[PDB]
Image (cartoon, rainbow, N blue to C red):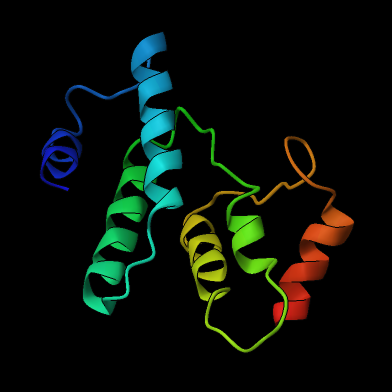
Length: 121
């Protein structure tokens, strides 16, 4: 949290883009940060979501938005647990800017991606 807040604060100067390995590390950071973003504690949960949204609206140029885990995060069935909240709220984060949720060009077919989105609707 502290080191990423520090590097993100250094925006306008030292963007993480234009360098290959810097971009790859940024992408692993993003995928890892969405991968573990669910904490039994709601305040730090909101905080982590804010970290992710700051990361994605500050980098924005090594695009690489990881689908297929937001997808499997809302794709859960048996609606008796708030397990799908993470995927829909991550999707809301990525939508909160101009990012397009173009599904089936890297992951699972839109006809079932959006299907599970609606089923949890």
